[PDB]
């Protein structure tokens, strides 16, 4: 059923577009200045703030870039927003940029300080997908969350409490949690946790276990390709009428759109452009915890690890100066595309059950058997391509 | 009358055999792989589930053991089953494996969590024979139940209620209960309990008493030697045609059969084979609450207590891995054999009557006077052998 799902989400994409265009028309920005991922970000956040303000806005004068600090009627923003969505709320829409930000943050930063202070192992990076994503996120907003993400929450919710209506949350938060697991025991053990009203260290220690079980017996976590507002604004302005022509966040749509996007970015004096583009590209698909090998394969070019990456962050801090600042054109095109999946793959004390399953598991264990990559011409999911990694690679752990 | 009883039960044994063989022929297992108590179990449970599914199936490749997770048409299973029993249901047959599982569980595990949560003393182990045995078990299925087993039920049935047709159950459940006792007062006091429609703590407290009376003035509880499906499958395949040659569950038949069985078992890296065999052997005769002294006497070799036993359970959990897994040949042969009995032995406020009887009772009080053990040649019950326990023994309480 390509009617609702493909076209209803198109309508949510149209809104973001239209809005971005309106909002650019207010700031009286130029074309080059509306394609500046920097300005786009600021706008996106102005809105999510107002629906739950001012921000940094960069301008282009003969030669150099001028940063403007501006403020807008928090309500005016809310007004312009609905105008674009037919006076609707389109929570989906706000939630969408709510994720684009997430996926950018899960790739720009490593959230160790928080994991440890929670009592999670810092090496549990690949499980913190969407830890930045405000709880306000929608129902299809949490589905993108990693197993580890959920645990950090419950553990804090529990840690302060064990240190009224709050209950329905906890059970559900677990049901979701449990719905991440895709194996008997995994599933069953979550229940054994959800049994206690005042779950103390008994649980505190057990979920942490299950957290680690997912490192081997992963769960189902959806990935959503959420592009910057500018990309959708520009597309809408170019005539693309997505609600009519349909759009996806896990199909070929997002890659194809990024195959023509003209996004620019501010870039510090010593930073590497190629390295900058990489970053953004990984935020456009939630590939911050993907196997670098595959990311590079699909990308078309080296996908260098975080450490070796030359950049501190896409947003420009108030600290920096504009004199020594310039801007490059972001390389967002990719070689092939792939169905962003949700599945994690698979081959007494319920712990034992898992520990026993954990064991038989080898890192070499092939997942998504038969699934492959698609050419950018292959609109339909017709012919798949299987990658062979016998190759001089460059790692697998972005972090 | 050795016609119906000996041959009708043979026919139920043929069914299990035949079926196991058919079912092995489907899974395309090998001879060694059909003798693996592990696989046998899985099959047995696949069936009891379907008559009231998939399971763990271990395979043998060059060197190492491969665990397959498989699923079968719940109805297909039911189809193959009847095919083996002449299109009959042979509830007896399912009930038989229903017990083999029971007797294995009453020996592999100690069910304390449940006794206490019911309000029974954890030290009432020797009275929980068949607590695992689904209520679906047949009429000759409950006869195997310990006095304590019944109490845990009524107490829960009562505890939730006191906290329509359900009545005929309660009275009968007591009549059975009462039919366990083999002394005046014991018998009479059960009636005094069965008098109340809504039996509250009045009863709750009284049966618990009677539970403890059985620790001294035991009741009649039948023991059934129920071997794994593989053992009967293998036997049937070897030509033994039990319905014609007769078979028992409380005679020499079961021991004799186990004198030639070639059963193999998966065994964890640090576990003791000799210790593994012991376990299974005790499940083959419901000797999980027998006096270790006698068990070892008949066994032929030390029957070590549960604590000192090196093993966690015969079934392999999903947690574990196969790399560090190997398999041994189970020692199920015994020195002598003995008529598995049913009898527990024997020498105002009806409580008083019992308490007074309780008293005169000494642990040294000899039971089954004159009854002895038989050589494995002594097919007939001809010549009995009396054991003398003056000896450096190793305990009496498996638990």
Image (cartoon, coloured by chain):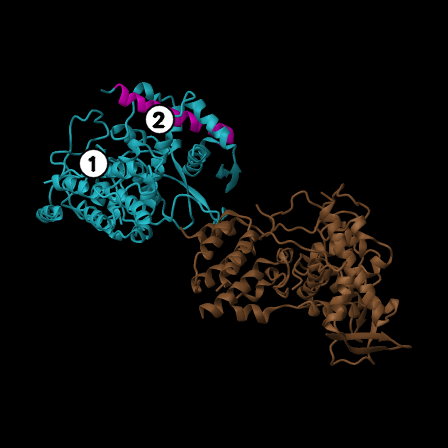
Chain colours: A brown, B cyan
Residue A312 belongs to the span the image colors magenta:
no
Q: Seen in the image, is A162 located left or right of residue A342?
A: left
Quote the CA–CA distance across marks 2 and 1.
28 Å
The picture places residue B194, in percent across and down from the top left corner, at 22, 41
Q: Seen in the image, is B253 located left or right of residue B370?
A: right
Q: Main secondary structure of the magenta part?
A: helix
Secondary structure found at label 1: helix
Mark 2 neighbour class, 10 Å CA radius: few under 14, some 14 to 19, many 20 or more: many
Report the residue marked by disc 1: B179
**Quarter of image, res B246:** top left
- Magenta range is B3-29
**Quarter of image, res A333:** bottom right
Q: Residue lying farthest right? A: A62
- Of all chains, the one bearing label 1 is B
Select label 2 or label 1 by which is in front: 1
For the residue pair B83 and B233, the one nearer the viewer reads as B83
Residue B8 belongs to the span the image colors magenta:
yes
Q: Residue at x 78, y 62 (%)?
A: A83
Q: Is residue B61 visible?
A: no
Label drawn at residue B13: 2
């Amino acid at each position: 059923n390509a009617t609702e799902i493909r076209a209803s989400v198109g309508k949510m994409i149209d809104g973001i577009g239209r809005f971005y265009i309106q909002m650019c028309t207010e700031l009286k920005l130029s074309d080059y200045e509306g394609r500046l991922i920097q300005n786009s970000l600021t706008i996106e956040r102005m809105v999510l703030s107002a629906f739950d303000t001012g921000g940094p806005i960069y301008r282009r004068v003969d030669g150099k870039w001028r940063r403007e600090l501006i403020l807008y009627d928090k309500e005016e923003i809310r007004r312009i927003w609905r105008q674009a969505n037919n006076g609707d709320d389109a929570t989906a829409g706000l939630t969408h940029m709510m994720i684009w930000h997430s996926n950018l943050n899960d790739a720009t930063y490593q959230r160790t300080r928080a994991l440890v202070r929670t009592g999670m192992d810092p090496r549990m990076c690949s499980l913190m997908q969407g830890s930045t994503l405000p709880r306000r996120s929608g129902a299809a907003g949490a589905a993108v969350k990693g197993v580890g993400t959920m645990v950090m929450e419950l553990i804090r919710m529990i840690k302060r409490g064990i240190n009224r209506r709050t209950r329905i949350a906890y059970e559900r938060m677990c049901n979701i949690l449990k719905g991440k697991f895709q194996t008997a025991a995994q599933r069953t053990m979550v229940d054994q946790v959800r049994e206690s009203r005042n779950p103390g260290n008994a649980e505190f220690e057990d979920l942490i276990f299950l957290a680690r079980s997912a490192l081997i017996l992963r769960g189902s976590v959806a990935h959503k390709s959420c592009l910057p507002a500018c990309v959708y604004g520009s597309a809408v302005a170019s005539g693309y009428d997505f609600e009519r022509e349909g759009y996806s966040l896990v199909g070929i749509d997002p890659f194809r759109l990024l195959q023509n996007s003209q996004v620019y970015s501010l870039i510090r004096p010593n930073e590497n452009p190629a390295h900058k583009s990489q970053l953004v590209w990984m935020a456009c698909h939630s590939a911050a915890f993907e196997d670098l090998r595959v990311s590079s394969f699909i990308r078309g070019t080296k996908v260098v690890p975080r450490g070796k990456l030359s950049t501190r962050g896409v947003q420009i801090a108030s600290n920096e100066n504009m004199e020594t600042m310039e801007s490059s054109t972001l390389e967002l095109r990719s070689r092939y595309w792939a169905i962003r999946t949700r599945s994690g793959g698979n081959t007494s004390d319920m712990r034992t059950e898992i520990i026993r399953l954990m064991e038989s598991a080898r890192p070499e264990d092939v997942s998504f058997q038969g699934r492959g990559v698609f050419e950018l011409s292959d609109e339909k999911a017709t012919s798949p391509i299987v990658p062979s990694f016998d190759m001089s690679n460059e790692g697998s752990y972005f972090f």
